[PDB]
């Protein structure tokens, strides 16, 4: 059984419990339910993020919400229904919203400053899509020295094209991108309840 | 049954760049991957494809930037040991700049942003190892600076990695997924190096 | 579309599967990577030989490694790095090494005795350089009544001079030398995986 | 400007004049005129062999003829016209004939004995076909320590197939095979008259 | 008193303070304490480099270290004691090290790229030996359009031979080589403290 | 009592090269040093010794490369005035190439590396002006390309230069120190031109 690079280098870390982490929810937006990027596993993932949000709000764990700012008439249009939060994952009680324009939630934003104000090294990162904004933000978090913990069940993606007319299933892309992050960028658990 | 890429959906897609109009970025073509602890199964096949790009770039005056990972003493990418050295067939020649890095992101704590800026080419052709770590991370980071990235699938390689429930993901399946991911929102992808000539 | 002499003589044979063959690897030495004969197609050909070696070791196929014995200060110097096996193609599991001093791997060597003891009439021949040690050794094998199989992609050569200060490209030399072997000395396939 | 291996090794040698050599004529047979292998350059090449044969007979240079013995109803059939020498390159009384069954004119024959008896280290090798019997016999001569000289114009060959329904022209085959022999097995000249 | 070429050409420049400069430390290595090149003035010069290093670290001035790679087991032993930094002048934090094999620390190195990345035209150059690696590196820096400042006290050299079995003292060589640099390649001060 | 050179200590020293085996490289033998603003006290003595090397080289078919400094209008080495011209006794003759340079390093922004490679001799004999600036810089640069340099002390000259605290370093003291420095790690040194004939 192959070891992770984290294990080989001695720089690995256990999955962080929610109660000692900052919860970072990435792009829980209506585009993934009724827009151009309807994710087949959205409801299952949103249910798992809700389990984390409920436990975090009950314990006073910090929650940061990332929203993608699309363009007029495009994906995640902020003037349109597709740009809004999924109703079940709206911010409450002044939980901060970070508006981003690139897959990297740190890039051109106040995210770094906000996570520093909370003072927790451990980030629990969840949301969409696993292979783009989530993976990119997790990879960028390593450069600042954060530990990232992900639950596989709390992120989701879609089918994407491969070379020569092929298709890569959402489930195969998810498995690969979660394994890649587990290799050198994060601690991975299967389910949200493992972090409670 | 045929999904679009985000680049296609956003209208921001771009053609694969010809090597002649690009800066060639080679990531971590080091001896660790041949005679170290991370012996990649597809190293030779991929190094051959990088060699095709290197040979063509040297003949055309195309800029080549070599990235070298600085690891820890006596171990992975040992800076004072054979495992840290470039593969002999992909050694830099005079004039070709080397960037030494410590993290997967070749931009992070390095002069890479500066060098690519001074070359003045928005198109990067990125190749090297490993596909899912330093390559993917560096390509994703290039998007934040406004670079266009082109990759040949055959010019990158990786290794088997563990999954949940004591599974293994094969190098081939990790490569397929990680290239497709970059094709969705971070790069133009071609099958083989000769398509960039 | 001209016929081969093997086809005209009715003496043609199918490409041998690796599982029924002795795998013969010619001069996979550092001369060709870091010495005076750096072959541009070395890595592509070493990758294809590696496919054959992995499959041979998985099935108990015998592997014979030929190593050119050069002179001090010269090509394939046995006391210098240039004489040693490429690491990814080195002998494992006590696979035998045959040292040779001429292009013909049989000349002044134990090669005939070793092949005879394996008791397999089918040889799969790969390595370097296509037009010199590989071609010569394949042609010599016909005198002993071996059948030879080659993959085009598992051999490589270099640019060589012609009359009037011309240069023959490695690709043109390879194409011609593989076609000449296919005419009267071997079964030819494009790629290593076709012998799996 | 690439060097030959003979030059890199310091083992090179100049073309031998005919007067210091043994002339070895390979398979100058009727098969190539009226049989199944009608070489497009037969007459031009047989003319150049003729130049060397005439010069040799006038100066008492030894000439050894090689004749391929095929099987009844096959290529080089000895039981009909296609096995016989071209009339213009027939042996004249005193000149010995080596009859062979393989491409290597040494294999199972008196050739080594005849060449040792003439006591000339230099062989001039000419005839048919360049890539098969000529190339194989020249390569085999190296193992005995002979120096070989060929004139490109006194050898000929035919179109042969390549992979995927391709064809290599006789001229391309001839060019590559003479260059391959020039790299490590022979000194090459363009024309017979250069050896006079 | 005679003018420098920098004054005559009006291309002169004042000594740069440490706060506006990149600090470049050349070959502060164990060779000069316990190897074949024991500089009589090493401790006094290393003390003055230490003043600059301490001040640069306290004020966020960038520091680049150059290390010379010599002979396995011998001069500037690359992975042995003699090749290591003097313990008091070891790199800290993310201070970059340039390894060189020539007196010119720019030649085939990343130095130009690292200095350009720091964005400061003014270099303070110190270390060993004044007349060889220091002088060569300062001269080379003129071709890239850098301005160099040297403190005489923060460089050292050794006695060297002249013609006729003569000896040039470290003190005379230092005076001459620092003045040569002042003439066309640098701004000179007596002591490290004048740059604080 | 007698210290060793760094070249002796490293085992990579070489003897002085005879003129007959060398390319002769003559640096900035120009009228500025005779009738301009930089009148060298030792110019005539040095020019006599360079003349000996030029005469022997011309006699024996030894290649000669002339380096000339290109100054600015109205400045030192003005190419538009007499001060930028060659000293009459050291003018180039038919087929001897001239390299025009803007910096002390004669290789920098010039075709000097190309010309020297075209003559195919590893041994340069370097002479001319000034010892401590263009000569010293050019000899130091030569090491980076793998050349061996030979100098005659008598075939170079410099001038008095200021030191710290209003002091003066004499032309002779500067010469002795800069020739010794080149002998330490950059060159084989002889006393006079006739030792190379
Ligand atoms: N006789 C071989 C020819 C291979 C040519 C490769 N250059 C075949 O039929 O496959």
Image: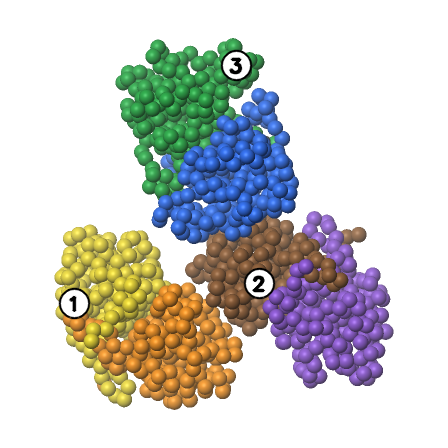
Chain colours: A purple, B brown, C blue, D green, E orange, F yellow
For label 2, the SS is loop
Q: Does residue A36 appear to the left or right of A187 in the view shown?
A: right
Percent of width and height locating residue B4: 74, 56
| Residue E115 % position (x, y) | 46, 74
Quadrant location of residue F97? bottom left
What subunit carries mark 3?
Answer: D
Residue carrying label 1? F191
Q: Which residue is mark 3?
A: D77
- Specify few, some or many for label 2: CA neighbours under 10 Å numbering under 14, 14-19, or 20 or more: some
* Between A65 and D76, the one nearer to me in the picture: D76
> What distance separates the C-alpha of mark 2 from that of mark 3?
69 Å
Q: How many marks?
A: 3
> Spatial distance from mark 2 to mark 1, Cα to Cα?
57 Å
**Viewer-proximal residue, D36 or C110?**
C110
Q: Residues within 10 Å of mark 3 (few under 14, many from 20)?
A: some
Q: Nearer the viewer, mark 2 or mark 3?
A: 3
Placement of C174 over or under D170, stated as above or below: below
């Amino acid at each position: 059984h192959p070891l992770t690079l984290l294990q080989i280098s001695g720089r690995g870390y256990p999955p962080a419990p929610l109660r000692q982490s900052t919860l970072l929810i990435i792009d829980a937006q209506e585009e993934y339910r009724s827009g151009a990027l309807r994710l087949p596993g959205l409801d299952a993932a949103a249910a798992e993020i809700g389990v984390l949000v409920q436990a975090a709000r009950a314990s006073g764990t910090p929650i940061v919400h990332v929203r993608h700012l699309g363009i007029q008439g495009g994906l995640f249009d902020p003037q349109g229904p597709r740009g809004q939060f999924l109703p079940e994952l709206q911010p409450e009680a002044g939980e901060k919203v970070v508006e981003k324009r690139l897959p990297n939630a740190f890039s051109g934003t106040e995210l770094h400053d906000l996570l520093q104000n909370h003072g927790r090294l451990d980030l629990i990162v969840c949301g969409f899509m696993t292979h783009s904004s989530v993976s990119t933000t997790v990879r960028a978090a390593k450069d600042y020295g954060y530990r990232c913990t992900l639950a596989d069940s709390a992120c989701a993606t879609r089918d994407i094209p491969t070379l020569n007319g092929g298709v890569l299933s959402a489930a195969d892309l998810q498995r690969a991108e979660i394994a890649a992050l587990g290799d050198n960028f994060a601690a991975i658990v299967a389910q949200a309840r493992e972090l409670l």
